[PDB]
Image (cartoon, rainbow over all chains, first blue to last red; front, top):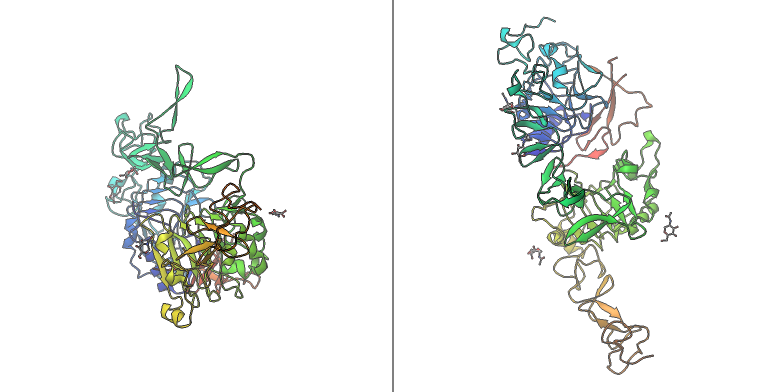
Length: 550
Length: 50
Ligand SMILES: *[C@@H]1O[C@H](CO)[C@@H](O)[C@H](O)[C@H]1NC(C)=O
Ligand SMILES: *[C@@H]1O[C@H](CO)[C@@H](O)[C@H](O)[C@H]1NC(C)=O
Ligand SMILES: *[C@@H]1O[C@H](CO)[C@@H](O)[C@H](O)[C@H]1NC(C)=O
Ligand SMILES: *[C@@H]1O[C@H](CO)[C@@H](O)[C@H](O)[C@H]1NC(C)=O
């Protein structure tokens, strides 16, 4: 119930070893479920790791390498799911945890509760001072074959009660076998050796009893405390009628859960909370609920975002993929601009992006995931290329954020002109030393949830902006503006002609006469005759609402 | 140390001022040592707080 993201650094770390330690603490303290990888690399001998006792579960892999500390306190870790593996093979990798000099290193693993490794193998090798780990029956902990499950002197023997398999020297250090020791009738795990003691087939880790509500962890989905293979579907087959019937106890699949409702920003397909519609279907709203329905004739231009489908491999928009965005109106995924995207990645022979090519985004109206701007061409002062962007769904978040604009010196205004909705996630606009209009925006008007925060730090001081005349146009409401001019408001103080706020419509004078559709100035039908001498040309839309016909 | 510096070919491997390192073990494992401002497998991402 206290979830964190975890790193994807592998063996990479910070040069400052205290900063490396401080980062480990930052990322993983008070976290129960690591929703990704638990990477513990390059940690000094002295260091306190007691905070790791918080960890119960790891979604991806566990990498413990190049450290010098005596003991690994993952005493509450039960399951490693191995959804993503180290070197695409190991769910658990513990290696080189000593100093080559030969002073100190890892001596004991506190994994007495690690009874499940769902996918992947175990690589415990090159740990000069590690004891007892050799005695571990990993074959019991790994649920499926993984042609890599092995452990590679002057070590104490296991306690008598341990049966030669233990994590440490004491009688309280015995390895709890939960699979090989079961009755020939258990198909899963067990808490004893008789048929009475088998776990439900859906229990991961182990159990405290026979029911699907007695699990330590779920193999698949959690439906109100019950470990299920699938959620109750919306339809149910009746065997006597040979027809599908409505199941009114149906629940929606969201992540590893059966939920009474999908998050508002997510789409509903089947009895499931998805992030994107299949290429064949199109997103439609029915009583506030986004759903996948078949296309009228031709499906809208939805494009793979950075880290999705055709761009799964991608980490940033670059010269090699900028052209995959021609004519996109919707981005199924994220848009990320990293330093190596804008300024090129020489090692992988990718040239710096052509700043003109960033105009491909002028067609983009929606970004379903997140917008992450960590780099931008220096000659570009704003994000006017995103002048048509209306929604950021936040169906995917980067550290809980749906909007990131950081370290950008060249930007002086934002210019997200069409922007009206940031459905989920928080905003992080920091260290853009010359940015100036951000402080006027009532970001709250863009949010859907009340849990949505805003982190605005170290941009140009609001006082400095005001003194240099970087203020909103008088026709802007108290909600703010994206940059200078009347076209850049969040809402108008009076009337509006298209994207620009004005004082009054062309009711009695002007090239094209207009009627007021309550603050929106709409041009009279071309058939209406231009009425002079204080007369209105039209009193509504269409040729029926004319004053005189031309 | 278990680590050695990379060749000049693998200089551009770590970006944003990251220092490349290889591991002496018998394939060879590569890693980046990042400046406090950056992270990721190749120091490609900015570090962030608050
Ligand atoms: C290990 O798991 C059990 C049940 O899942 C829990 O009682 C406990 O706090 C953890 N046990 C120890 C000895 O830390
Ligand atoms: C399943 O979910 C409930 C919350 O809905 C939680 O109290 C319980 O920990 C869960 N059971 C397992 C085995 O994860
Ligand atoms: C994009 O659409 C325009 C018109 O809206 C058309 O001229 C062009 O062929 C399209 N180009 C690509 C590369 O999809
Ligand atoms: C704008 O911020 C205000 C303070 O004036 C807060 O009431 C509100 O949630 C947003 N106001 C409106 C009228 O949407």
